Amino acid sequence: GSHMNSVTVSHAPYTITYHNDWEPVMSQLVEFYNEVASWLLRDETSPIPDKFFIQLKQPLRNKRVCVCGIDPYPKDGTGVPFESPNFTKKSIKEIASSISRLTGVIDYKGYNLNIIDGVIPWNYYLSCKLGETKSHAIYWDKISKLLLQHITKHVSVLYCLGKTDFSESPVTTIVGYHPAARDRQFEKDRSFEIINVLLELDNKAPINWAQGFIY
Amino acid sequence: GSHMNSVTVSHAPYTITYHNDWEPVMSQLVEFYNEVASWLLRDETSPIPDKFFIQLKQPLRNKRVCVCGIDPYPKDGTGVPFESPNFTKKSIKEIASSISRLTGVIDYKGYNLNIIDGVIPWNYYLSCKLGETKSHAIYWDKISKLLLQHITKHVSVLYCLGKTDFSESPVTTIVGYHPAARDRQFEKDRSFEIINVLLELDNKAPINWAQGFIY
């Protein structure tokens, strides 16, 4: 569209297009990515390099919640965090169930966090070696820090998913269970519910979690 | 007592005694404080140098909430954050009122966060030039970071008081209004209430806020 820009990097995907809201961090991102990309690309990745940076197409100014996982699905990442086109990945399924139990919406065939007003779904690390979670942590390090720090300047609540997974200006942060953690249904459910209360506290409009449903 | 240690610093207060729980950070603290203390001491301070570090006598392992202000009272700091022996400072008075409105406890003559099980009250900066808030920020910088980072390794919830005041491993953090902020009574009240819910989420025992009352 007519509200975006792009930068050139020396390695695949060679071009990153991004929303104006990301501009402040883009030249630092280019530097860091040229330093590490040769080492990232040696492996088949989730997602493919062409989809590493597609979430930078998302605007930040209209966002108030960030739902953040550690890295993309071991396989089948689309570049949109949590996205599972054919609704097969356990993570998004469990998230959908919580929102079902919270909202009362019974029947659905999918769920996607990328279509909820005021929500940016996010992967801390933007890739992993195909089949291996956290396997690209070292490469993403400085970029992961830069991008999250930028996000927290816009959103009012950061919700990170996975306690042991997640081992400058403080924002309201919640660290809850991994979406696929066993026998922690109450805590997973309640964790989502709290977000809207915290937003009320910060004088922000609630999130309509039901917007994520696909029928 | 028989569960504590001490270190020698080159400037006033010359000796810091501390609980075993603080040990990991103490030699880094000594280094930083000898680098900056000459510049801190040129001014009359709140609290007096003898009371800068008295909160390091507090154990951390039994704590699950940190209630954290930016720095000590402009005047009359005792070394215990939020402490006001004669119950005169607006900050602790407003905190007491919230807990009154939350709990239903009507009659009291004081309130102190330092006597509540599972709560560590905390000043981010450990001093200020007498009469000037944030006036010692530059001196405390690296120590302030070190000590808070250590605290968040023990507590499950960090509650920071003052949005514009507060401009490695993520813990559950709430940033609420300054205790003395005008016409924000609901948000101040509700902010405290949320802490116990978050603790429930993290499978921790609630805080008994009424323990802070003095009759």
Image (cartoon, coloured by chain):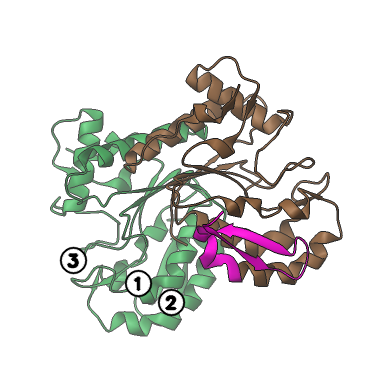
Chain colours: A brown, B green
Kindly check if marks 2 and 3 are in contact, taking CB atoms under 8 A apart as contact: no
Indicate whether B63 appears above or below B190: below
Please provide percent x and percent y for residue B153. 53, 52
Nearer the N terminus, badge 2 or badge 3? 2
Which sits in the foreground, B133 or A96? A96
The magenta region covers A1-27
Residue receiving disc 2: B33
Indicate whether A132 appears above or below B38: above
Which disc number belongs to residue B47?
none
Q: Is residue A97 magenta?
A: no
Alpha-carbon neighbours of circle 2 within 10 Å: few (<14), some, or many (≥20)? many
Marks 3 & 1 on one chain:
yes
Which sits in the foreground, A113 or B161? A113
Is residue B19 shown to the viewer in this render?
A: no
Indicate whether A92 appears above or below B142: above
Residue at the spot 73% in from the left edge and 61% down from the top edge:
A138
Nearer the N terminus, badge 3 or badge 1? 3
Which disc number belongs to residue B137?
1
Q: In the rendered image, which quarter is residue A157 located in?
A: top left
Q: Is residue A16 magenta?
A: yes
Under circle 2, the secondary element is helix
Which disc number belongs to residue B75?
3
Alpha-carbon neighbours of circle 3 within 10 Å: few (<14), some, or many (≥20)? some
